[PDB]
Image 1 (tube, rainbow, N blue to C red):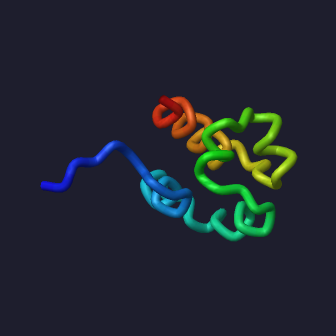
Image 2: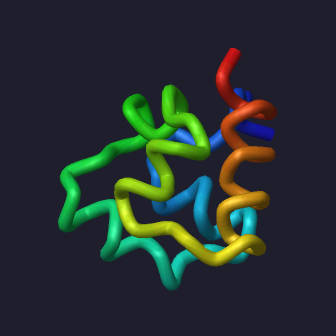
Length: 67
């Protein structure tokens, strides 16, 4: 199998956590994977992610893939 070291773009990360419905929010804010992986919960709020569920999934993903 092809070596893998995690999502290589934001859409891939969002698909992995079931959050593709937020892809456009990040595209309109011009936030790519590199920037996403630096975000705080406060940042996610500023971007437009207010619902508890998606915020929690995204903060968990950021912790997992930050590296």
